Image (tube, rainbow, N blue to C red; front, side):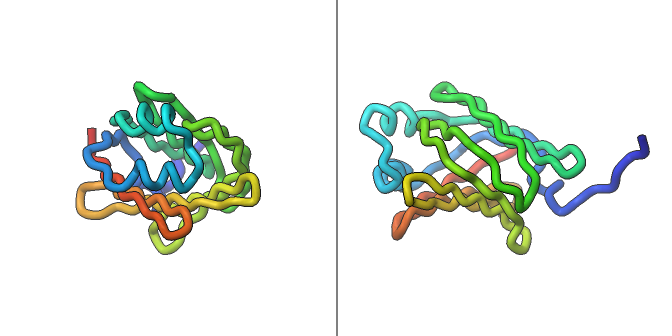
Length: 139
């Protein structure tokens, strides 16, 4: 083994904690999440751990609602069971520095964008015309 070099995506790596959220209930309604799941999911303040190992990126969410972990290679579709229990087909790419995560299920699509802004990691969730913005800080 030699030590690999870094990458772009190193700006995302770390341990992050949710500090604010706007319009997440409306985003979840647009997605189709039911009432009791929305209420409990909307209270959560997860910790998100992002790591890279070679070509494989892992995003772990540790949450009082539902722990999740996804591992992927940019550009390469994978199966994902979301925190709210959708079975989706996901592809995550980089668009100029923004991680773009598209989920497809039941003929529907939603996109979750993740971007560094100052010391924060801003997450924009989009379903049709409804956007939610979630802001994470370093833990």
